[PDB]
Length: 330
Ligand SMILES: COC(=O)[C@H](N)Cc1ccc(F)cc1
Image 1 (cartoon, rainbow, N blue to C red):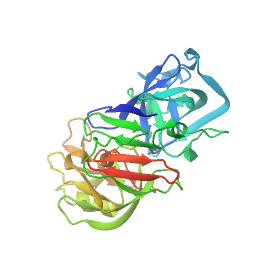
Image 2: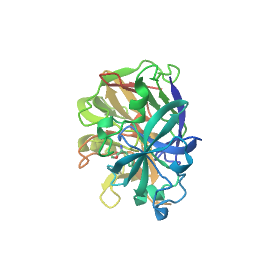
Image 3: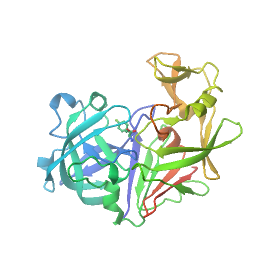
């Protein structure tokens, strides 16, 4: 089996991407944020506190002939940005791009935090990290990918995120038309539950490549690229007037600037992030200070190759018995 679904940025900045997901029978289509940094498939639902729903599409298990309460199971999750949600659990049929899983744990929100409420375009999350991070208690549940893996033609999924444009998530096959050159594979540690890997270094603009090991995670549910403070300072030093603002919460730069590219290493290969990918626009409406797309990971405790990095590549999440990541230019 394979699946193929289009993923669409939620706004003009590529703050996140949403992918339609069919849940239940008859199908209820919700637009979920596919997140390679978490392991819960959770949705706004008929159970979500009414005051915490503002424009989302909800899953209503009572309208699904295939929904079953997973008796006694609860979930509660807290993300890196301080957002959170919690609730109870149903099993139901879930399809992505024509690939169907029966008996998938669908975590129904009773509570969502303000950031979720304030984002009308995201109906929930579909976690694609390792199932060891799934928060369901007392019986941990598997991700959609882990449940699909054994029906797939190949135990893989790929992320092909667009820059200010739609992209694709494929399951079970590698579209050799979707990238240029070859795919460079690199080792993964699953010890923390993430797609954790080690970049071989970086360059700023047309500068020399610095060979240095940068451990981090491939995380489609994080907008920006978070790297060590040394690396980030070296980048923003090439942008006249850029500075770290404690008031704004990161590096800002003059909106009149032209940003340099940023290159990261994957083994002996190189992925180039164009400068325009690093522009996240005015800090507030009408401001001439713009927010940077490369930020320090200091105090996060991990480096994060979020969408700014991943959208510059065709990314293979290889879920074979020994997982690996692959990156290709495109
Ligand atoms: C722990 O948070 C993360 O970094 C997730 N992988 C991405 C993520 C960030 C915010 C959010 F509301 C949902 C998901």
